[PDB]
Image 1: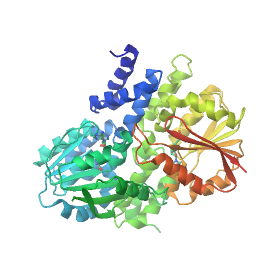
Image 2: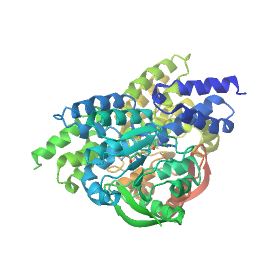
Image 3: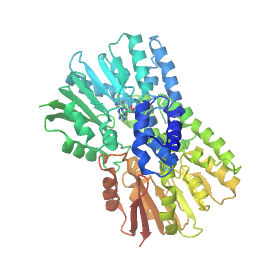
Image 4: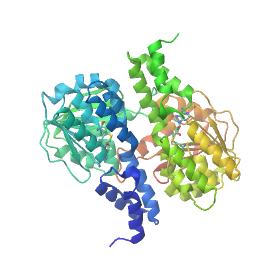
Length: 260
Length: 260
Ligand SMILES: Nc1ncnc2c1ncn2[C@@H]1O[C@H](CSCC[C@H](N)C(=O)O)[C@@H](O)[C@H]1O
Ligand SMILES: Nc1ncnc2c1ncn2[C@@H]1O[C@H](CSCC[C@H](N)C(=O)O)[C@@H](O)[C@H]1O
């Protein structure tokens, strides 16, 4: 069985306001992976909180989610167009908003007309996509707040797009699709389990993949993250896959990848 | 002069709740660096918001700051010891809490007894330090919320420690000290201006430096960030400085650096 003081620490994690919208099985998995590394379960709890913030919490806060909820409601009015204002509330979509036009111009012909699109670790990106005519996507994420907002917005707009819970460390999505998006995802997945990026890429049942990385440059060249991600990606990419194209849009390094 | 629509976009940034505690000169500098790269000043505004979130906002939210305020008040009662609970509210200090004992055991003999310590881009770290007997530090940061909390806590505890506003892209701190801490700082500084890390290290007026990097590992080895930071650091380190020691504590790669 489980130690009682360990369960109290896990309980503090599971009842935390900040984690209320993370998949509980993910919270538990992270904590149990860390629990054998600290003598004090309260130290495992702090370590799990940090881990969970790094992999999902930092992109969107708890009350910015209710704020995003109310903004997207004003967008379906068709007056406000605070659609930009809502998508600005998740760190990964706000990063993409200023280059979104360039991004769709350069990526959408790869996806194909009316493609069935899987958006893996989707955050709020399926709302951005859907606004730009890509309305047949299936998002998935461990952040049930993201999932909920996507489904609500899609049903209100008449999109076929939907989202569902998914922890990519314990599930390789089995859906069929024309394309899958792995945007700003592989580094944080590989941080959670060595080899997991290559295992995911080799097993997805979509012939075209869009894989992207953040270039954490902000006017200076930084420590060279873009080249480091590129080298790593080219080294782990399964031999069954081939890069069709590479380019950088608004501090996002984008790869168009084809199944050979 | 400045374009009026550009100033309206800057004004939206300067009046934003999320930025209310960032140094205004820093907000303006970031926006003016980006303003010549977008045709629409509202796109420069979104880009500046993203930049500013990456360099300072993501570590601590706006209301977690009032929460930290109320927790630290209960700690000076000497009953609650929610000191751990407050320091858990800034991402960089919560990362360090579980290894803090190991961290002080391994770093403090380098600082020296009753050292005068500069804490550059200090976040809430001077409160963590001060609790552990390092009570003569001068923190500095662009986050005036951090600065305010540090000064309030220090005066209530009787510490000599203080903090002040400082933008490390436009100022090389001129203070004299026994040691300076550059913790989880050089990558984000170098992302803002190429060469700025080496210029800062070569000009600080302290004979001992503690320089640290996040190892963004979470159970998997990720893309190899630790080795990448190590290689970069060894390449940019000014020849007037020498690494005395290196070790990793709680996903922080730590260098003890001596002026030769
Ligand atoms: N193990 C995991 N399984 C599923 N999603 C995960 C995950 N680890 C992190 N995530 C999700 O990965 C996302 C990283 S931010 C990238 C979001 C989106 N692809 C975009 O580019 O806009 C977060 O939404 C987080 O919830
Ligand atoms: N140009 C700049 N000048 C001063 N501080 C900066 C800065 N860019 C980012 N920062 C600060 O750098 C910090 C990075 S988080 C690291 C905080 C602290 N050293 C610790 O390890 O706990 C944030 O507090 C942010 O406010």
